[PDB]
Each structure stands twice: as C-alpha cells, then as structure tokens.
View 1 (cartoon, each protein chain N blue to C red):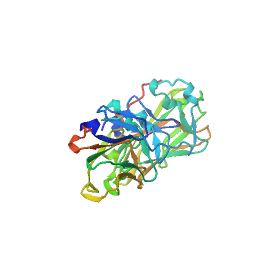
View 2: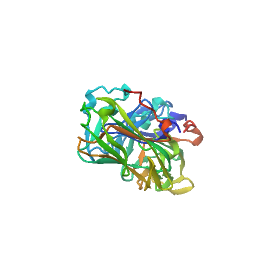
View 3: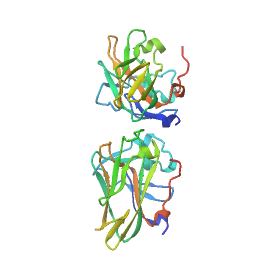
View 4: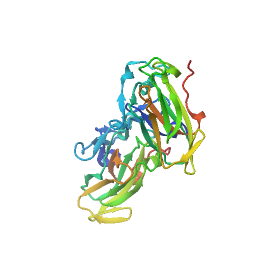
Length: 184
Length: 184
C-alpha cells in the first residue's frame, strides 16, 4: 500500500478535520470536551519549516496541567510507525517547558524540550517505529503484552505543561515516512 | 542570532497576542485578572509615529493607583536590551502624569512625563541596556546580585497613575534595536 492507503489512524489535536499536501486526513479531535484543554493561541503566528497550506496542524493544540493521553485500537499484526507533531508557540528560552512521552508505559522520548531543539514558532516531529507480533508490542528494544489497544501518554513534570499538536500511525517502516526539511 | 530569534520575552500590556512588522511576537498579557487594571480606551485614537499596522500595541495599556510590576526569568548569562513602549492617551499638558521606573530596585528612568517628551496620542520608547555575568546584574553603572529573575516596577507618585503599553527583552546591544523615527 502507498501513503494515504497505509494510514490507519490520525488526529488534529485541538482542531477540525484537515487533509495535508501528502493526502493524509487528520480527523477532528476525539477528546473535545472530554480530557485536557484545547487552544488556538498559535493561529496568530506563522509556523516556520512546515508547508504553509498545513500550518493549522501546528497552530492548534491539546495541553493539560496533569498527565493525559490517547487510546488507539490496532486491528492487525504488523510493522508500524508513530509520528508526533509539535511547536512551541509561547516560550523562547530552554528549560521552560519539558515533558516525557510514554507508550504502554515505555518511555520513548525523555525530557522533550521543543524550544531547545528547533526554536520559537517552528515545526518539530518525533518518529517512533514499532512492531506488533505474536501477542507482543516491541519498541526501542523493549517487549510487553499487547491487548488490542495502544496508550499514548504525555507526562506532567515540574517545567510547565505537556502538549501535542497532531499525530498519525502508518503501516510500514521509517524509510516510508515524509521528513521535514533540514533547516530547524 | 538575528532579530526575531534574539527576543527571549515580550508582552502586549492590556491586550491580546500581536506580531509586529519586524516579526516580534508580543504575547497576550500574563497579568490579566491578577495585578493592576487593563484599559482599551486608546482604541478610539490614531497613534502618531507608530507604524499603523502596529498601533494596537499603544492603544492598549495596564495601569494602577499603587506601585506594580512584571517578573521575568532569565536563563543564560549575556548582554541584553530592555525596550519599554508608552503613549499618553488622556492628558495634554505637562506635570499631569509623572512616574519612575525601577529594575531590581535601581531607578533607571526618573520622572517620566510622556506628554512632555512627545505630545498627545504619540508613541514614546525607552531603551535600557544591561549585562548579566558572574552572578551579577549591571545597569547604568550600578551592580547587584542576580538570583535568576528580573523585577520591572512602575512606581506611584503624586501625579496620576503609572502605566505601560508593551515591552520586550532581546539578546545583543543597543545598535541592534529598531528605532522610532525622529520626532520634534
């Protein structure tokens, strides 16, 4: 399967439906009114490094002052890649907003500091490959029992609030994923 | 670092987010509902000497009948410049509204009289260089211990109320700061 056919699940956090330049449909946020807080504060800002037709993905977010997450049903075994999209639309110094990302309890991004990596009002993506086979989840060399659902968590620490802007899961391997341009 | 990348902290007092013609993002006021009073009285007036796309910065203010201020975290040592933006949208004579500005207790502007300097409904900026090095703040030839936070105070005297319209801090020196056009 090619790119749009290979996407099994995708969300525009804090926002409405949007189809990007690759043909990927980011669905309206299923956690609206349910957990966390939506914000459209970034809609006043141009977002560097992303395509301008798609900057609405990075201008809307879901955030919270406590740990929160999304649950994802996965129907079939296979190889998959999770892509997480972020932007820092408020701070402009390091160690102001910092948080962990976990997958079924496994820490998969430690101490994410969006400003430190890319600057202010600029796109940043994390790309995480995984496998689901023989009743097991495998990610970053760690293995545990898979029950049918994936839990993606954004963890509250001491430095401001965890957040996410958009996310998708595709069948395949890392060479299949479109990459942001080098200029960060 | 060039101009937008060099701004570490910026506020539109009494107002919402706004990006100016130089690309500087003035954030929504963090003291809303907390300290002092917001006013949009100036939104009825054209502001002279400002770019017209940016006059909303000077049409909105925070003021108070007692002393008040902003606290600013500074993460790294270096040379910096503080820029303070003002307009007098009510009085049209001298010695009607007069106030001091202090930085960590140091008086850095004595007896500011906005009307006396520029007239009615006209932009006026103060430009204050400083250094943070070896555990110390240095400003206007005076030195004191720096703990990690800067306190910017607007002081109540006998002649009406202290106020501010917008403010920002950039890494660099005074030659790097955009200047208002010459005025009588």
